[PDB]
Every structure is written in structure tokens, then in C-alpha cells.
Amino acid sequence: GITNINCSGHIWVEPATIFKMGMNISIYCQAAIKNCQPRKLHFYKNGIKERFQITRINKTTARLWYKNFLEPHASMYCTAECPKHFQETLICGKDISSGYPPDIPDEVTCVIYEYSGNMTCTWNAGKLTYIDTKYVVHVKSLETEEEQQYLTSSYINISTDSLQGGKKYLVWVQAANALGMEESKQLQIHLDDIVIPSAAVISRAETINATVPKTIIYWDSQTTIEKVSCEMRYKATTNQTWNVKEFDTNFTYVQQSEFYLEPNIKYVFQVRCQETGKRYWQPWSSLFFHKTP
Amino acid sequence: EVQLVESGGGLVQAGGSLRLSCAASGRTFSWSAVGWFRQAPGKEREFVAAIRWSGGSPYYADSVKDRFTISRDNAKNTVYLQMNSLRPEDTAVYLCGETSLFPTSRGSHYDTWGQGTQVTVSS
Amino acid sequence: IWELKKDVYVVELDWYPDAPGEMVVLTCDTPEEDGITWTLDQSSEVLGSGKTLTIQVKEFGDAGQYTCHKGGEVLSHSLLLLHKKEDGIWSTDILKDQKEPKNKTFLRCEAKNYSGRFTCWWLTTISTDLTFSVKSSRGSSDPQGVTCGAATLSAERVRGDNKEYEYSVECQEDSACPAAEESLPIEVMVDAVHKLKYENYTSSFFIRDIIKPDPPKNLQLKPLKNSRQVEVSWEYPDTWSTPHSYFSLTFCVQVQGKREKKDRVFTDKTSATVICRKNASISVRAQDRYYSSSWSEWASVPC
Amino acid sequence: PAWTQCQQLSQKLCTLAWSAHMDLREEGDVPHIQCGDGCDPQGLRDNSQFCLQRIHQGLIFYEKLLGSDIFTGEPSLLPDSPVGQLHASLLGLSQLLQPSPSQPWQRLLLRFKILRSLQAFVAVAARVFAHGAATLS
Ligand SMILES: *[C@@H]1O[C@H](CO)[C@@H](O[C@@H]2O[C@H](CO)[C@@H](O[C@@H]3O[C@H](CO[C@H]4O[C@H](CO)[C@@H](O)[C@H](O[C@H]5O[C@H](CO)[C@@H](O)[C@H](O)[C@@H]5O)[C@@H]4O)[C@@H](O)[C@H](O[C@H]4O[C@H](CO)[C@@H](O)[C@H](O)[C@@H]4O[C@H]4O[C@H](CO)[C@@H](O)[C@H](O)[C@@H]4O)[C@@H]3O)[C@H](O)[C@H]2NC(C)=O)[C@H](O)[C@H]1NC(C)=O
Ligand SMILES: *[C@@H]1O[C@H](CO)[C@@H](O[C@@H]2O[C@H](CO)[C@@H](O[C@@H]3O[C@H](CO)[C@@H](O)[C@H](O)[C@@H]3O)[C@H](O)[C@H]2NC(C)=O)[C@H](O)[C@H]1NC(C)=O
Ligand SMILES: *[C@@H]1O[C@H](CO)[C@@H](O[C@@H]2O[C@H](CO)[C@@H](O)[C@H](O)[C@H]2NC(C)=O)[C@H](O)[C@H]1NC(C)=O
Ligand SMILES: *[C@@H]1O[C@H](CO)[C@@H](O[C@@H]2O[C@H](CO)[C@@H](O)[C@H](O)[C@H]2NC(C)=O)[C@H](O)[C@H]1NC(C)=O
Ligand SMILES: *[C@@H]1O[C@H](CO)[C@@H](O[C@@H]2O[C@H](CO)[C@@H](O)[C@H](O)[C@H]2NC(C)=O)[C@H](O)[C@H]1NC(C)=O
Ligand SMILES: *[C@@H]1O[C@H](CO)[C@@H](O)[C@H](O)[C@H]1NC(C)=O
Ligand SMILES: *[C@@H]1O[C@H](CO)[C@@H](O)[C@H](O)[C@H]1NC(C)=O
Ligand SMILES: [Cl-]
Ligand SMILES: [Cl-]
Ligand SMILES: [Cl-]
Ligand code: NA
């Protein structure tokens, strides 16, 4: 009627309506008008009638052929020339997509930001697929053997409350789309080894006017973890190198780093920390500038 | 009133060939067609070929398709009949007429006629 | 083959060189069974013998009046017409394409108002052996009633070396609802026969699409103070629907002597102010204010 | 109702509905102001309520379509296209009265269809408001 299209036949694609980008494809249009042997069968791509690679197979079916189809989307529809009408009668239409099969997800990593209460698992999905790719994250306990699955389109947060059976789990990721399906290697985790302490931030910057200038840097974190190692970077904005110092800090008290420095230039500062020995680090804190007197 | 004038006839020998022409003064209708008939002695005039001024495939009699070919020239407004490989059984008066019911082989469907030209084939 | 009217049948012929045509069987309308012979048109050559005649219809020569005879007298007639199809296209020789609004427009219909009365036109270069037949209705499934008059010659002009003839029909919807919003379209269907050549034509439309109000009424001018300006005044045409507070109109006014692309001004009021020049003229059209149907013709006055 | 307010913005819809505005047919629910719904001049003197009821039902039905995936989704509307203004004004006139999913390839055909029918609806509606503001003010 007015709120709906009324097809009078059907259209199909070989190999499929979703196919690998750059492949040869054949589009078939089969008319089914009552009381009409189509004089001609036309194809339209994005509203533009096609003029090449069309062959009339039999009295009711026509075939359009494309070499190396590169568009990721395209709206197709075909029509019929009926002797009893001056208009072309719509047969049917269809949206076709092109893309790529998914890569094998690698770089699978699962961490627990402190206090977050959930575990954040990410991965490298690989090259672009263009088409709707879904990801399934499997979590299995090496103890109780019970497996939970989670569907997602990007990354995922799993709640620690759901990780009841033990502290040793296996995690792999499955990527799937119309054109293919791949699976990551299993990554095993120990919920004690994948913790990243809560953010450490720089508060202020004090300089003392006592002969050689000491620039005390105040920074702190709200982490309950005991053994913690940290790193801090400081370069002169004019410079393009990073100078760093390492510390095994005790966050019971606010830390203060004592620096002998040069006057009257801009500076930058950043910090990151980890549970000592563990695999993962914090991200680098935001930039903290400080000009000296 | 359209006027039709035949010409090109004469005496040729078996195996020869003529090209008759039918000069028309105009066209009753855009879809009008000109047809050649042939009237042998003793018999009635029989259809040979016909062609529309607006083109398209012509309409030939059952047999003549191989030897005879009909063509047109809208500029000069004349219709031609190329006769090849003539036999003594082709001797007759060749007339031309205009019709508004292409395709047709029936004389009474042709409204306007010429007076015809004589073709004689002698063995 | 199918019956067009009493004792008149139409054969659909897909013609091309060496086409086989259609096999048609005719049966003499008689209780008798033996001693029956057949003719075609006014020729007395017998074509077959028996109560039934089988013919291979493949050209206009095979059409016409087939008649069966017994004992030297006539029994029944059968007239065969042809609907010629060539390369998938039905013939359209009888009517001329008017090309307004769209190409392939052989029937052109207009309405002066929403009353439900409309008139259709068509053109032909033929003057003899020509017959038309016009029916109409609203909707196709469960059709409502639309009565039409007879088609008759209305005009006759020149088309180069041919005279062009114009036929027209008056039609009226049995039960009209001028204010309503149409959901199903009017269908006009015209059969045409010329000698042995059958053809038919069609046209679908909503009244609102084919509406063309008559020109503005009582167009007049009057000078103004100082500068050479004029006040143009007009009224609604009589044929237009009523009341005018419900069926409103828009108007276009333009000056034009002898690049008058800027002389046009539009308004919903029934008078305007314009500037006149030597030997120039003022003219005004009318269109339905709330639906862009067709403009009327011009109503003009000299400056 | 405020006839002068509905008349000025109902004629605004007509201008918009045609500023935006093929030859494809199909082998083959929507509210039309059908005959007997009291929207002719006579019906408004008897009772405007019958007509304002049907016009209201139509303004919300069309606004629903104009705000659905048919017009919002892909392919996208041009920058100058005024479909948004229509949707803005359809809901504006519905407040003054009484305080399925489409595939991309269909939508260009649907957009043309819907706007073709909207023009005929908005036309008659501008006529009743023009008649009401001029008689039943
Ligand atoms: C503008 O021009 C166009 C083109 O010319 C017109 O289009 C034509 O319109 C006519 C009339 O409507 C159509 O003819 C009719 O077609 C009917 C359908 O035919 C097919 O389906 C039926 C299903 O029942 C089959 O039986 C038919 O099979 C027949 O044909 C095949 C092959 O040719 C044979 O092998 C079979 O043996 C059959 O013979 C078709 O497949 C058809 O039912 C109908 O036939 C009846 O009527 C005719 C006379 O009109 C009789 O000769 C016939 O015997 C049938 O009679 C019975 O049925 C009628 C039904 O009303 C009863 O009244 C009788 O008493 C009896 O019981 C007829 O043939 C034609 O097909 C169509 N052409 C095209 C291309 O579309 C437009 O109409 C025209 N527009 C206007 C406005 O005029
Ligand atoms: C003309 O040529 C076409 C194309 O070769 C033929 O089309 C045929 O159409 C039917 C329609 O149903 C197809 O059947 C299909 O079967 C599969 C199962 O195998 C099913 O998944 C589909 O839904 C459909 O039912 C058939 O496959 C198809 N043929 C080919 C070769 O693709 C048609 O039959 C030919 N002849 C005529 C007279 O149309
Ligand atoms: C798409 O079709 C074309 C033509 O059928 C294929 O072209 C052939 O390509 C190979 C090398 O890839 C050549 O050796 C052949 O000579 C080509 N064919 C012709 C007729 O020249 C092409 O391979 C096809 N590609 C895909 C992805 O299907
Ligand atoms: C635990 O994970 C959930 C999601 O899995 C986080 O909550 C989401 O927060 C975003 C806002 O950034 C909302 O849009 C989502 O709707 C939330 N989802 C749920 C399920 O609540 C949550 O932030 C994580 N825990 C912490 C402490 O951040
Ligand atoms: C997983 O949890 C993290 C942490 O809560 C979410 O990250 C936050 O996302 C919101 C989105 O608006 C940001 O505003 C916050 O700054 C992010 N961090 C925090 C600490 O809230 C993340 O969105 C979640 N992802 C999923 C898929 O659930
Ligand atoms: C930048 O800092 C590094 C490390 O202190 C130093 O060697 C270098 O001279 C500084 N300047 C530039 C231009 O690298
Ligand atoms: C951390 O600092 C507090 C406060 O000075 C101190 O009591 C505690 O012993 C320190 N922890 C370690 C491991 O040295
Ligand atoms: Cl292929
Ligand atoms: Cl990769
Ligand atoms: Cl003509
Ligand atoms: Na014959």
C-alpha cells in the first residue's frame, strides 16, 4: 500500500547477499507478475538503471553480473516492462553488503581495576570487516569447570561477583560474522595477578627558595594494596626526551618526590603504578605542567 | 489523395534482375505502408511484399523472401522492389498500393493504387 | 480470442516475420450441422465446409467478417478484429501522444472544480471507419459508479499535411464528495476500432491532480496617483467550487511587453499593484491554493 | 479551537509539503478524511468536533511515519530537505487540537509515497481551518 512495498517476485544473490569485498557476484531477478510475460527485466543499483552485464536467462528470470564489487553497501531492485503498463512494475529489492571475515582475536587481556568490582577484558579484533561482527567471550573456571558466555560488539565488563568458583579461569574470545568465524587462544588468569591499583594523581608542585631549588611533587593514590611500585616521568617541554625515576612506594602517606631542577622553564609530569611483580600497569596519569620561578 | 506511380519495368531475360520503384506523393498516415502486388495474365493480383514508411521489418509473401527485397527511401518518398533471379513465371503487371493495416496481403485492404508497370521475362 | 461485443471478437496477434499467429476456431450459430460453408468479408470464395471453421490468424488479411451459409442463405456473422502486438508493444496508431503532462499520454482529462465532473480529450488523424467506446469508474476491485456521455468531435485543426481531429467526453461521478480526500483513483478506459484494428487506452488520476480552474474573472485595471502604477483586480471564476472561503485560490500576475522572468508576483488576494509600460499587457492565472494542481489559462488586459 | 492559529500554520504545512516535492508502479490502513467525516462546509456548521477528531488522528499518524526509520535512517536526507520542518510542524498543530521497520532500499520509494499522500491530507485540512477562521471564528 502506502506504508509498505509490495513485491511481485523475488531477487537473490550468488554467492550470498553478504559476500567478501572485491568478489565477482551474480544478481538474479525472477518476476512473478500475474498476466505479464516481462518484455524486459531491469536492474537498478542505488536508483540508477544498469546497462551492462545483464542477460535474460529465461522468460521470467534475468541475471546481472558484477566484476570485483567494492561497495560495502548497495541497494538493489529490479523491475519489469509489462505490455499493459507504461510504467515499470517493481519486482523486488534487497540490500547487499560486502566485507571481510574476522581475524583471529589476539592480545587478549583481562584486568581488574581496583574497586571497580568487575573485570575488564579487551582484545585486538584485527583488520576491518565492514559488516556486523559479533564477539563471544567465554569464561571457564579451571576448578569447577563451569563456563559462562557473554555476547558483545566491542569489549566487556564481567562482574567479580559472577566469578565464584575459584581464582583460576580460562578466557577465550570468539569473533563471528556472515563471512567467517575465528577463535582466540585461551588466556589463563589469576585474579590476584591481574589487579591494577586505583589511579595515582599529582596534586601540586612546591619550590623552596633555599640555594639549590628543590621542587617537591605531591602525588597520592587511594589504593589498599600494600606492595606497590611506581614510575614518574619528567621532561622539559622544550626537550623531547623522557627522564624517569622508579620508586617502591608506601601509599599510607602522601608521597613527595624531591627534585633538584633548573629555573624558569615549563615542565611535564606523569605517574603510573602497579602491584609489584604483576604483569599489568596503570595507564599514564594526565599531564601535570609546572613552570619554575 | 495520395498518388502512386510505378516505374522500372521492362523486358529482361531469365536469370536477370530489375528494380521497380513506386514514387508516392505523400503518406495518408504516419503508420501507412506501401505494398507491391503482381497481376499475371488470367489470374488476380497476388501480394508480393510491403513495408512501412516508419521502418521496422517488412512483410514478405511466403516465397519471394530469397529473391525479392523491398526497401524504402523516405527522402525521395519512394519504395523500391529489388527483384533478382527472375523466371518466366514472373511475367506480370507489378502494382503498388498504400494501406493503413500493415501487415496485410489482401488487396481490398489497400486504399490507393498505382496503374502498374509491366514486367516481361522471356526464356 | 475474446468477445468485445455481440458477435465481435478480438484476436491478439504477436506479429513478426514468419510468426505463426493464433489458431482460432469459429462455430456457426445454428442448430443445423451439415451443408455449411464459410466466406470472408464480401468475397464468395468458399474457405471451408462444416459447422466449424479453423483459421490461422497471422495478419490483418485473416481478419474481418467470417460468415457461414447453408442452402444459399446466410446463417451467422463473426467479425474478427486484431489487437496487434509487435516486439512486446501494443499498437497505438489511432490516438496521438499529446505529451502533456507526461509522455505516453493519449487521454488528457481535466476538471474545472471538485464537483466530480471532468472532461477527457484525445487526438486522431483518422476521419472514417473510426469508432470509440468510453467507460469509467472509481476504484477497480469494488468499483463505484461513474457515468460518461458519448465521445464526439469537438475540434479540428491542421497537423502539417494531416487534419487533426479532437474528441471529448463529459463524465460525472454518481455520488461525489467534493470536500473529501480521495483514496481510490478514477479509471477511464477507451476502446478504439479503425477498420479491423482494435486498440484500447487507459488513464488513472485523482480529481485533485487533474484540476484546472477557469481563468480569473472580470480582470480590470485603474490608474494610481503619480508614478505609472496600476491596480489589477479580478474575481473567482463561476465554474470554480464553492464556497470560496473553503476552496481557496492562488494567483500569479505578470507584466510582459513584446526577459520577463521577474515580472511575476504571487498573491492570495484578489487584486495587486503593478507597473505598466508602453504597449505592454497584464495577465493573471489561478491555481488551487492548498494543492499544486494545474494553473488556469491566462486572463489578459492591455496596459 | 484557535482557527486563526491553525489556519496560518496549516497553510505553512502546504508550502512545506510541496517545497520538498518516481514513475514506478507496484502490484497491489492509512487514515483518509473519508466522506461522511463532517469536514465539508456543511459538516462544520453541524459539528466541527467530528472533523477535528479525524484531522487529529491523521496528524499523529503521519508524524509517526515522518519520525520513524523510513525518514531518519539510511539513505540520509539532504541538508536542504525540509522533512524535519514538517515533522516539527505536524506535532505543533496536533498540540493546538487536543492537549514494520523498513529496509534501506525501500525508503526512497516509501518517502515519495508518503509525501504524495500527505499533500492531499494537508490540503483539505488547510481548507477547513481557512473556512473556520472565516466563518466560525
Ligand atoms: C485492452 O486490450 C487488452 C489486450 O487485448 C485486453 O486484455 C484481454 O482481455 C480479455 C478479456 O478480459 C482476456 O480474455 C479472457 O481471458 C480470460 C483468462 O484467460 C486465461 O485464464 C483462463 C482461466 O479460466 C484460461 O482458461 C485461459 O485459457 C484459454 O487460453 C488458452 C491459450 O490461449 C487455451 O489453451 C485454453 O483452452 C483457454 O481457451 C487463459 O489461460 C479467459 O477466462 C476468457 O475466456 C472466457 O471468455 C471468452 C470470451 O470473452 C470465451 O471465448 C472463453 O471460452 C471463456 O468463456 C468462459 O468464461 C467466461 C468468463 O466470463 C464466461 O463468460 C463464458 O460464458 C465461458 O464460461 C478470455 O479469454 C485476455 O486474456 C486479455 N489479454 C491480455 C493480454 O491480458 C483488455 O481486456 C482490454 N481492456 C478493455 C478495458 O477492454
Ligand atoms: C529460469 O531460470 C531460473 C534461474 O536458473 C530458474 O529459477 C529457479 O527458481 C526456483 C524458485 O523457487 C528456485 O528454487 C529454489 O530452490 C532452493 C532450494 O534448492 C530454495 O532455497 C529457494 O528458495 C527456491 O525455492 C530454483 O533454484 C531456481 N533455479 C536455479 C537454477 O537457480 C527457473 O526455474 C528457470 N525456469 C523458469 C521457467 O523460470
Ligand atoms: C572474476 O571473473 C573474471 C572473469 O570471469 C576472472 O578473470 C580471470 O582471472 C584470471 C586470473 O585471476 C585470469 O587468468 C583469467 O584469464 C581471467 N578470465 C578471463 C576470461 O580473462 C576473475 O578471476 C574472477 N575473480 C573472482 C574473484 O571471482
Ligand atoms: C561494571 O560494569 C558495568 C557495565 O558492565 C558498568 O556500568 C555501566 O556504566 C555505563 C556508564 O559508563 C552505563 O551506560 C551502563 O548501562 C552500565 N552498565 C551496567 C550493567 O550497569 C560499571 O561502571 C562497572 N563498574 C564500575 C565500578 O564502574
Ligand atoms: C566498563 O567499565 C568502565 C568503568 O566503569 C566503563 O568506563 C567508563 O565509561 C564511561 C562512559 O560514559 C566514562 O564516562 C567513564 O569515564 C569510564 N570510566 C569509569 C571509571 O567510569 C566502561 O564504559 C565499561 N564498558 C562496558 C562495555 O561495560
Ligand atoms: C634532553 O634531555 C636529555 C636527558 O637529560 C639530555 O641528554 C638532552 O641534552 C636534553 N636536550 C635535548 C635537546 O635532547
Ligand atoms: C608505610 O608507612 C607507615 C607510616 O609511616 C609505616 O607505619 C609502615 O610501616 C610503612 N609500611 C612499610 C611496609 O614499610
Ligand atoms: Cl559469480
Ligand atoms: Cl592481527
Ligand atoms: Cl498521422
Ligand atoms: Na490466409
Image (cartoon, coloured by chain):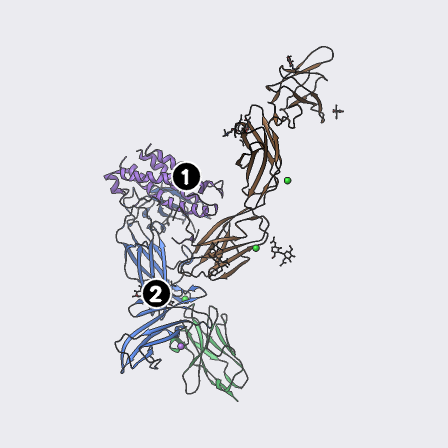
Q: What is the number of the mark on residue C192? A: 2
**Left or right: A59 in relation to C47:** right
Q: What is the secondary structure assignment of the residue under circle 1?
A: helix
Q: Say which chain tag 1 marks.
A: D
- Count of numbered labels shown in the rendering: 2
The amino acid on which the numbered mark 2 sits, given as a three-letter code, is Ala
Quarter of the rendering occupied by the N terminus of chain D:
top left
Residue C289 visible in rendering: no
Q: Is mark 2 on a helix, strand or loop?
A: strand
Which residue is painted at 48% across and 47% down in the image? D105
Chain A: drawing colour: brown
Q: Is residue C118 above or below residue A233?
A: below
Q: In this view, does C61 lie to the left or right of A183?
A: left
Say which colour chain D has. Answer: purple
Q: Colour of chain B?
A: green
Q: Residue furthest front?
A: A144
Q: Please state which amino acid type lies under the numbered disc 1.
A: Leu
Give the CA separation, mark 1 to mark 2: 46 Å
Q: Residue D86 carries which label?
A: 1
Frontmost residue, C79 versus B118: C79
Up the image or down, B39 lies above or below D42; here it is: below
On the image, the x and y values in percent for residue A93 come to 47, 51
Q: Is residue C8 shown above or below A188?
A: below
Estimate how packed mark 2 is, as few (under 14), some (14 to 19) or many (20 or more) residues with alpha carbons within 10 Å.
some
Where is residue A160 drawn, in percent x and y?
54, 27
- Provide the letter of the chain coloured blue: C
Residue depicted at 29% across the width and 57% down the height: C170
Q: Are circles 1 and 2 on residues that touch, CB within 8 Å?
A: no
Query: Few, some or many C-alpha atoms within 10 Å of disc 1 (few <14, some 14-19, many ≥20)?
Result: many
